[PDB]
Amino acid sequence: KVFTMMYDGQDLTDYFLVQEVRGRSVYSIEMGKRTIAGVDGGVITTESLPARELEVDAIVFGDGTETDLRRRIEYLNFLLHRDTDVPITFSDEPSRTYYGRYEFATEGDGFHKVTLNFYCQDPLKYGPEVTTDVTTASTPVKNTGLAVTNPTIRCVFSTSATEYEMQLLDGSTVVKFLKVVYGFNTGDTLVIDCHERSVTLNGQDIMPALLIQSDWIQLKPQVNTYLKATQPSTIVFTEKFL
Amino acid sequence: KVFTMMYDGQDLTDYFLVQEVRGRSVYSIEMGKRTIAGVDGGVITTESLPARELEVDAIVFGDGTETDLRRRIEYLNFLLHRDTDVPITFSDEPSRTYYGRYEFATEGDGFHKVTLNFYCQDPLKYGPEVTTDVTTASTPVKNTGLAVTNPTIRCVFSTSATEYEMQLLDGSTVVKFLKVVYGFNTGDTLVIDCHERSVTLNGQDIMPALLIQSDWIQLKPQVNTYLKATQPSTIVFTEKFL
Amino acid sequence: KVFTMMYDGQDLTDYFLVQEVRGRSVYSIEMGKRTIAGVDGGVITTESLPARELEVDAIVFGDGTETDLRRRIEYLNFLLHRDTDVPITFSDEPSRTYYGRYEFATEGDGFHKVTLNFYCQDPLKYGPEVTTDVTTASTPVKNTGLAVTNPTIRCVFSTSATEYEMQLLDGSTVVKFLKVVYGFNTGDTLVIDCHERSVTLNGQDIMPALLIQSDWIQLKPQVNTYLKATQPSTIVFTEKFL
Amino acid sequence: KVFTMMYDGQDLTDYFLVQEVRGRSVYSIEMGKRTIAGVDGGVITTESLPARELEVDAIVFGDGTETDLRRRIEYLNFLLHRDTDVPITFSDEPSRTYYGRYEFATEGDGGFHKVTLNFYCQDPLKYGPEVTTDVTTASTPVKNTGLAVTNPTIRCVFSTSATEYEMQLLDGSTVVKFLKVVYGFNTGDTLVIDCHERSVTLNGQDIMPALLIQSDWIQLKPQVNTYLKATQPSTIVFTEKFL
């Protein structure tokens, strides 16, 4: 049972042997610094997380023959070239998914050492998704991840509806909220924040219902978020890490 | 009793082992030099203290397992990423605080060597704050720090007032003064030489009272500053070092 | 939960930090080679396992002060100097004990890198001890270790005895046997194939009873050893590895 | 289909990954040189093939865990330590067997552990496919298809009665060497092994006195015919050998 790397659901480690994986240690920060002549110090103007570069140091294991090796590489190119971000996973870190695509290779020097470089537009790893029940009272919802997350609201109606609201609060003060005036019974409303949609009874997008520009929610990490809904709801967020 | 580093009140050394801390030796100076062809020498046009970069060389002590290490780093990222300057301290230098934020890491190659780089907008280390009483007689006020400070004159009235004054003298000759034309009893005035503001009864602005360009006062280091106030005052400064 | 090294039941890793432990990889073999001029090839004359040298690469974590460090090393010397072989263990390999003693250090050059060298007279690591019951029928006894063992046959009599025997068979053919001519009831016999001794009623020597050169028995690794005793016996061996 | 290395019938490459195998290139020769002061040149006094050292440069592939790695190495030691020469084979060179045993390892440096394993071969030669040729009652050419000198094996299953069995190595019509035996009978198989230097009957009973007079064992030179003639239709079996 060796170290496995999965790229778009393909086990790449069936084609090569992984020496080391750089790109997942202490993350760095892009800072905009501005300095003025004669004035001591500097000033941080901007701060952002750079995109992630995963660098896999591999050994392409040869099939004895030379033509067999040439053909393995051709196939490896087939598996790697992607025009869309893709789920990347490592066996040493379960419950974690990276989303990026292969970018470039740097060939090193008995056999074939290669550094495969993968680019991730979204610098964050995505972990297990957590489902919490939200009652008609102030409910604490703790974001177990280490980064701020956007949650999916889910309410499968028990009684008739007129106006559905998922209010966020600070003790007893409504900070942000989500409102929908379309009412019915027995079906599932689905307010996702990562993709920003509004599904119904059996999956139809009811976008006109979001009346006022009701603020998109976020769950801060290692801290409770107090939520109160009109009807017994469900909050699903996905744990995220840098 | 190991070497501890505190970042925003978090003991980072619970996550890594400190080899060495660069960034706190003989400070360098940014100088604007201008030279003219045919003219001997150069001319310093500007001089400023650059911002401070603290470089901590650490060993991330592993928890035996590989996934345990990946998760420790994830948490380390959580503790480090800050969007606001923060108090930084080292056990080897007590009564000293740096204000900055983590910026970037450079990983090296048995175990896991990392350089953590912290950026300080304010290049100065802040020491203990000193409060000295200034009497209605020439009072020596010694700035115990190693950098020039712009203090705060605080006076809480005992008797009635017609005009307040705080004077910086040279034996018996008024060098600078801070005359104020607004009087009352029982309330607090705060003359801030850093912020360049006036406060009465503890809140509201009294900017027009400082009549004539009533010179602002500074406290030079390792040297006495003689001050005489019209009413028993207090002088608040914080020791600073490069 | 850091990597712990135990030396004579003392946790040495309370005094230093382990970078790496060399000395426990693919073992080498001392071979006596003899060559004759004009004669092709060589001849292995002798083969033996060299003694083991464990080399621990450590960082002596300082207590901030200089005198504190000098005193920690003094204490470290106290814990290390031994005039008798001692049990050595590493957290990464449980159920394994090395028997040796500290020999010498080679200091390297932020902090204090040291190689501690431990000498093991007995090159083998000792694992869990296994006790298997041997019946009056052909019993398979599997040596779970990776090295050949000379076990101990233990029999505590239930009925009267005239002659005891423990036989090593190949299906139904007695390969070796351990016949003993001295009988009684209620007491314990211990036939030690390592020490080559005989014990009755738990203490006294019964060496002349093993009549004919009644062959000594060994347990080969990863393989069954079929044994049949004249009375319900017990076979005690300790798993060993290189 | 990776590069496989077999040691005593155990696939060692199930435990490690082979970077390179040194020890099987142009073989060198041990030469005894003697020189005399004032006399130009030197004199070769002895010449012998040194024993072979095979050097396998491997990567021990880890099982993720640290304890799992420690236990793999322990097992690898179990598979390697031998007190007897053993058949060694490499997938890149089929129809070839080396006979030696593991001797010593020399370690090296992230998430994988580089090792050179050194194997010692008392017999410096590789053993290839074995060839069976029929030898008639007339001068028979027997060609040694190997690249080194071989010590063959003569097998003769009697059709008629015997008084004396002879195997003569000739040069046209001149007996250079020969192998006779005074023991006669019918219907059974006789075996003369020039490698092991053994005399064999039906159930392999030693006929030690058979090699009577210095009736020498002979050898088959490579890429060249060896002319043999037997008293009773025989069979010669030799094994191809290479340096």
Image (cartoon, coloured by chain):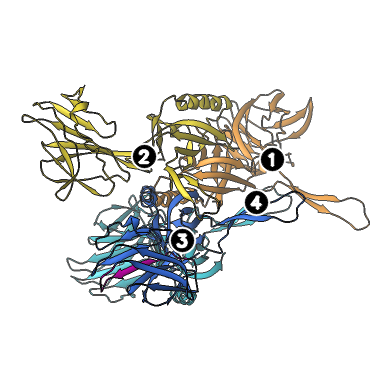
Chain colours: A cyan, B orange, C yellow, D blue
Give the residue at mark 2. C125
**Above or below A1: residue C168:** above
Per the image, label 2 sits on a secondary structure element best described as strand
Whether discs 2 and 3 lie on one chain: the answer is no
Magenta-drawn segment: D148-162
For label 3, count other residues whose C-alpha is less than 10 Å away and answer few (under 14), some (14-19) or many (20+): many
Give the residue at mark 3. D18
For label 2, count other residues whose C-alpha is less than 10 Å away and answer few (under 14), some (14-19) or many (20+): many
Q: CA distance from mark 4 to mark 1?
A: 32 Å
Name the amino acid, label 1. Leu
Whether discs 4 and 1 lie on one chain: the answer is no
Q: How many labels, in total? A: 4
Give the residue at mark 4. A42
Per the image, label 4 sits on a secondary structure element best described as loop
Whether residue D157 appears in magenta in the rendering, the answer is yes
Give the residue at mark 1. B210
